[PDB]
Image: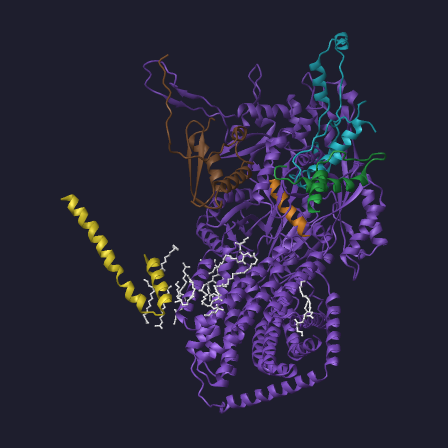
Chain colours: A orange, B purple, C cyan, D brown, E green, F yellow
Amino acid sequence: FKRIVQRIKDFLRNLV
Amino acid sequence: MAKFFIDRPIFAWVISIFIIAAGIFGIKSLPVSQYPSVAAPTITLHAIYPGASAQVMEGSVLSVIERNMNGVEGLDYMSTSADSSGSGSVSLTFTPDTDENLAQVEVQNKLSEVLSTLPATVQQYGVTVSKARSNFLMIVMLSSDVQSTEEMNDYAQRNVVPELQRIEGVGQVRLFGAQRAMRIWVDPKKLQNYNLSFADVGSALSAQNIQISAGSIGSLPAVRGQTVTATVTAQGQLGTAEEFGNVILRANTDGSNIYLKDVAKVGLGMEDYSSSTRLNGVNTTGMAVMLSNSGNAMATAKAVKERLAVLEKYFPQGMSWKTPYDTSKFVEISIEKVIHTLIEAMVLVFVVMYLFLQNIRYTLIPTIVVPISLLGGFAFISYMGMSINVLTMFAMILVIGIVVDDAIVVVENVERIMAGEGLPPKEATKKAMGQISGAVIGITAVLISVFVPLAMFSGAAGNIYKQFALTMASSIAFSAFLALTLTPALCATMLKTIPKGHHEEKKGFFGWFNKKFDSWTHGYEGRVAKVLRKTFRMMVVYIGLAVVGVFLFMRLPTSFLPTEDQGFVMVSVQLPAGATKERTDATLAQVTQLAKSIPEIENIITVSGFSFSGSGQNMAMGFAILKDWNERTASGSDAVAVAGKLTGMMMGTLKDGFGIAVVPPPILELGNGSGLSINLQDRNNTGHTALLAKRNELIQKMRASGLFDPSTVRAGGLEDSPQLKIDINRAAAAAQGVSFADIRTALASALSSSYVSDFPNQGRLQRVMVQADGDARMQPADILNLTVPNSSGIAVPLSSIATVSWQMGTEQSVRFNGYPAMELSGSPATGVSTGQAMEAVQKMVDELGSGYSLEWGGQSREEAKGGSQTIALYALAAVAVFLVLAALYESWSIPLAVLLVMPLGLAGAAAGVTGRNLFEGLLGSVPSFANDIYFQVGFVTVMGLSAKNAILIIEFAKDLQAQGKSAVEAALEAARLRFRPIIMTSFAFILGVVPLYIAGGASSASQRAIGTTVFWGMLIGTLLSVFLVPLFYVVVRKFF
Amino acid sequence: QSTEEMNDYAQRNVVPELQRIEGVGQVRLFGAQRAMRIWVDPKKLQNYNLSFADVGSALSAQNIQISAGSIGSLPAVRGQTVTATVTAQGQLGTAEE
Amino acid sequence: PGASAQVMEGSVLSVIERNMNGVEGLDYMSTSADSSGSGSVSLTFTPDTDENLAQVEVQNKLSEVLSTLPATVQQYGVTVSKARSNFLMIVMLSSDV
Amino acid sequence: SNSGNAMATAKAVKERLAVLEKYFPQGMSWKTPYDTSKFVEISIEKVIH
Amino acid sequence: YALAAVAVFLVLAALYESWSIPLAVLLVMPLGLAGAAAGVTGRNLFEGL
């Protein structure tokens, strides 16, 4: 589940 | 062609019926979503290596994977990211026109080559290759306030997730919660009491919980006479906590049988414990639904909601479902806006047509023709494989007006001929079409020529332009084809002859309006004659206007898209390094209450564990869902105002840590397109300290001694934090039996979790994890109390062979294109073009010694390429327009008189934008208009319309001179003849764009941008054109 | 610089850049990147009564990557305010080591 | 190996089948599991769907989902085939020696 | 590569090498004494003439 | 069958500039249907006997 979290925060990192 | 169909109305009707059928069929089979795909393909890796630091993760996993990725077809650039969370990722970006599926399969096949060279635990967990593209549709939340998050996550995974992904149009469902697991919490004190180790626990668990494969009786190579065969089955796996607690760790000779349940506590738990989510302050379980390519967003969202409503019946007491965000609402609103604008345009066209042509059957032709042209555009859009989304719907809205003109022109010309010569409608239609057919063909050719360039741009901006370009071009082409076939047939059939000898001696309103408009037309002709008599002065005035307009256009800000009120705000919370999850949760509760204090906020979703900066126990973020746009119309109830209020409250309330509220860019998949993003590479592998020092030097050079708006220049990582460093004496450890690998296993099971085996839990396999009791891993002094076995098998504490001290280490590491890198951000100071700032930073990076390079990221990679493509495309467009007009007029010099109207529209647009910016500044509102994509689209639209009007005027003027009139007389007569249709179309188009000028609500920023540009450009351009186009004709004839 | 150093520099800096170029199918270095080479003398092994497998096992057991973990990890007792990352080297990086 | 048809179906085949929804041009799916710890998932696509694109997409999804499947399946992997079930010919070899 | 172009690939390799030369250790240079695209370009030029 | 009839109607109307001549033509399709159905039924009966 760390991988799903990694995906969500990578997207968020990009926006701001 | 027009003459052919004037005598065959039923053939034209049949063709139009086929067009309507094709359009309906195309609409039936179009994907529906709020936005199309504009970003390039990207593949990510997402490996898990538990219990590791950024340096360990990077060097042991991410570099190893990265080194085997140079060679995949169509790779643009590549990056890595590692943090202290025990997980990392490798991101591969690809050149456009690369098949994402092929890229993903090739990346997976490359990973399969080096998978065996990774650490054993990495291979145990596996590496997930996926594509960054996400067609996000909804969030589904389950809230109980009674049962824990473990229960809700299990219930979701077992009941809700499988039901949602069986729905039509669903491409993927993702659960934002950890699965269940069997957790063993070992007390190291008891372990040392029995002289056991974590390795013993793991070995016993793996040996006593394993699948058995027995076989069958009487297998094929059987003895003679065998009559029965049977499958033999034995169960060798455990399924309950009581069963797991009875695992034998040491079978003593006396028969004591030290069990697993007297050194550890065994119970069902989760597998992460990292992230927590809440909705308005209560525990929740979130799910994300992603639409499939070729799926309909509205239908899928409705079906999902129906399914959830049905399933709600079986929820445990206290559990409820809610969907706080949905993207299908935006496209639904866009389609509703399209329909409303179409109805309003039809009504307005009817009103003006009846006011001018003084009959009701004249109003019937535009009503029939315009929807058919739109349907033909829809059919073309379906044929090309596009979809219905916000941009295509905006393109429809904007092309409605020009397709309306294409019919107003023909109807007005026919009505003029009929009222003038008194001919019957058939003869009048024949005459009018013989007059205007070639002009129509040339106009459609020019419109295609001007719109094709917008489909030739590169990148995400090109993808965005392609929507408008293709939709509008198809609609224009179909409108022209219909004006050449069906409009003349309708004119010749449905109209009735004007009573011969009638001078329109009307009564009441009609007579009065006729007289007043005739006076206006006469006054207009007098003013045009005055303008024509003195030509040098008017040419000087025109050059002045063109120069001023060009100057205004240049001095406009550059941007991509304007931020839009999408209905939510984001909050990012960051606490001092080393803070724990408890303090972060307290701060999140404070933020939740503050959001509650704001009426504009409907729901607040807070997630603990990671932030905008990154992951960590001190990181957190929140999503604030705003009320409906209808409920938020007064000043200060927009997304920016809500974000400002929340930020102001947070800066005064929160004690430990800080929070910031912002609104995201209009397109989430496409990152922020503002600022200057810098990657500072280390070519020589000097070290982290050297690269950090160089980054600090570059930041100083940019801020103190540069032109970058010093405020925004800052690093985009996460500063170093104190860490605990264990130093082991080789000699001391060798003196005892410690082997440095028993140390590895002991630490990996003590200070971090260990994944040992797998068990069945009511039908699905779930992990077994050994993590050690929390009381033995809280303080630094606990590290040296851990024990590791010797060769003889005795336990020896780490204190004897090791020491621990506080040090400074990296919290996060990133590589770019195979070198250690740092990330930086920036923004131009003021009135500074991005190009010179980029040259400046390149020079500064050069000032640093060799071994340190530079690389642009994100939008800066595209912005590095010059703007020569746009200039070249518009130059080619102008050349093509010139050639087409020369073919139309059979001249080389006449086309010039039509090109001189381009500055008029440009000046109108630029002046309108500048004036509205200044007015909003006076009102106190910050500027919101720039030279963005929507400005370019609107400029192209108004420029095409002005070109159409000029072409018609010049065509009429040229023919009159050929008959015998002088140039000046011909120009006067052409202006007098074209006055009425131009007034009609300008009125209709301007008032039809007015609603986009005062737009407010969903996607209203782009609406307002287009409205401003189009409205002001059209008004000013038409006002100047109706006076200057005859001047252009006269001058061009005199000169040549 | 000798051919060994240049070969290593090529493998680490030039080859990836070249094989990231469009139209390239494969890059072959007429050489190899560096490695830690142990050159064993069997006579000395006889003198000390050792074996090749002994050398291999000792190298494997004393040069590995250690993942320590963290302090105050996510499931924590009440009142925990300090979190940290633990680190241990466990790996050799020079010929003398 | 060692799993009943029910366990094989609920732990491996069902997981893959559920994640196979949303693949372009899919008509229907079926699974078959057996007492001997072997199983299979069959995906049928509409005609006018080319086998190669469907192959690539199905395999991408399978790789995406394999991250959780059981350990022994991951050891043996999952095989892929796309050939006609019906026979074209039967070739016979006979000998008396 | 299968479906690769010799001339374009050689030009890209040479440009990339020229760019990378800026980071070399001191005393290190680069050459391409063997190159099959030179014959192609010269022959094409001669036929054009 | 519906699309076949509609296509015939539209093509005839475009060919002859009328809405009634194609209507007269379409009246013959029931005769063909009756013939075909009667033939199939009759051959079935004859073979059964």
The foreground one among B64 and B960 is: B960
x, y percent for residue B979: 59, 81
Nearer to the camera, B485 or B707: B485
Expressed as whole percent of the image width and height from the top left, the position of residue B524 reads 63, 85
Residue B123, position in %: x, y? 61, 31
Tag count in the figure?
A: 0
In the rendered image, the residue lying farthest to the left is F49
> Relative to residue B983, is residue B836 drawn left or right?
right
**Residue B180: quarter of image:** top right
Residue D97 picture quarter: top left
Q: Is residue B132 left or right of residue B366?
A: right
Q: Which of F6/B925 is in front?
A: F6
Residue B79 can be seen in this image: no
Is B660 located above or below residue F46 in the figure? below
Left or right of B440? Residue B306 is left
Q: In which quarter of the image is the C terminus of chain B?
A: bottom right
In the rendered view, tell whether residue B245 sits above or below residue B656.
Answer: above
Q: Which of B594 and B233 is in front in this view?
A: B233
Residue at position x 64%, y 79% from top? B1026
Residue in the picture at 38% in, 32% down: D88
Residue B946 picture location, percent across and down:
62, 72
Residue B482 visible in the current orientation: yes
